[PDB]
Amino acid sequence: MKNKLVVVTGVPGVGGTTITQKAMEKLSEEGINYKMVNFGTVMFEVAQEENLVEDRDQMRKLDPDTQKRIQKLAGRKIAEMVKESPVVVDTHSTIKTPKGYLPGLPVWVLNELNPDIIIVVETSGDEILIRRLNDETRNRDLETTAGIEEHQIMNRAAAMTYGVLTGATVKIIQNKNNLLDYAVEELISVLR
Amino acid sequence: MKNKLVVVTGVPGVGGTTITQKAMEKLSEEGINYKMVNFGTVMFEVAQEENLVEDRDQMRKLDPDTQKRIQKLAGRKIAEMVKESPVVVDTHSTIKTPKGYLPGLPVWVLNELNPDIIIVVETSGDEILIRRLNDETRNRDLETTAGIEEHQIMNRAAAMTYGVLTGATVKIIQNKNNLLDYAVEELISVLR
Amino acid sequence: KNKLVVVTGVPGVGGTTITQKAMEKLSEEGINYKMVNFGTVMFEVAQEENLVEDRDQMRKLDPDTQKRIQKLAGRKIAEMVKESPVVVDTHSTIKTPKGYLPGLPVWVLNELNPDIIIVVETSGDEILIRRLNDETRNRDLETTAGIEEHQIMNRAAAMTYGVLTGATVKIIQNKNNLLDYAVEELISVLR
Image (cartoon, rainbow over all chains, first blue to last red; front, side, top):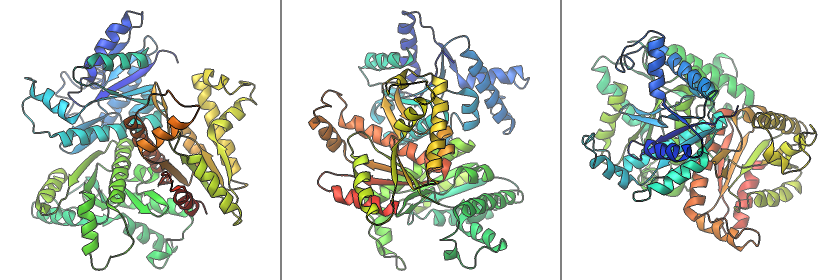
């Protein structure tokens, strides 16, 4: 099936969404119009449609078992979406929870999703930690560069695993400070 | 008491078992009583009821397809166990054999356990090597720190795959010298 | 019964090379492995389905059809282990502009059922220089960190194959001037 479906992951702060946007932006110039979607958002939308919530807070409290179903359906919806346009699913490779690294796209989601590319945007633990500091929305944690680095290591493994299970290729892009443009150009080459 | 299955993994010497023992102790006096059990142990117990072996090293040389049945059965037996008590499985992410790294939880075993967390305990290659050099009943082979770190790199990857194959969270706890109590407390919290 | 091992490594590691040196030895010891490149087998299937007639036409091959050939490939190689132990030469992940592509997707793994996955590697510096000196490869512009990243992703994928098929994952270093030690280690896991 034409219309590529890719998922752009990265650690909070690498600005995967940012370079994704500028890539779409710049790509649109050549008639290519990707549909960005946030996986967590889709589950929320499937929740409302299945009559199960009314806001993003009834999702966390939503039954653990049925939460797998919502993931399956959310994977179906997006799959159906590439029928009408190339899609970028903005989600996590692994979500860093206090209980540990949680897979953003478990296998039962990948079967319904069938991605073509898994982007893993990265940069230095240093850069990421500073970005979060010059960020007013944050200013809370104590996440060290080794922790960010460790996270980026697990995401990588998760991505590759996703790749093997889905056949999708895993692309690693470095979004380094004062070099945004190069990251963006890198991404554009893989989405085009 | 009811359900919550977890697997604690670690390379020999990191003391994943130890910190698990402490955690389980401080937990029983909180009402939470986990039944710990070794995956190797159960497989043996299972092979015996099937009258397949006498001693453990008899399973060394055991039919490849038999080992798969045993595993699937030992993962199922351990599975039923979560019905009457939260369980912690003491096992290896991968076993460093001279034939390479053997996955401790093959997909068919994962589909039986359906664990919730995959604990991965680590420390520097140096710390482990010195813990191995000092061990009395050990003193064998000649593994290098890089080797130990290689094993930990692979266990991390293995762990992550398990998480992707079951939706289970992957938590890395650092059990470093003279910091045993921080690791125990950290393990307790995820078992909470 | 016949062992089925798949050998991997980034281009330049001499992964195929140590495997050949290893087969010569195991041969004069009775054990005879049949080496085969997964890419060739794929092409072989395709050039029989009349879908392709040139190694290059494979690239142009349909994306869904590409999968059907990978399955058929695993099935042939699988059937090969009925006759002799088999070594499959392939990449854990092929480093493309689109990124790291898994050399053995799960639908291939199920047909293959390998017993051992081998990861042949060395330092970013050795690979890079080995490539540099080859009259053919002189302008790929991939740095040592680049190769190292590729090797990192190779381990992950190789490990995933093990988790999915139960196969063991043996990492082996093939460093300059120590070729024989790499070949030796390989012989130990193959016999």
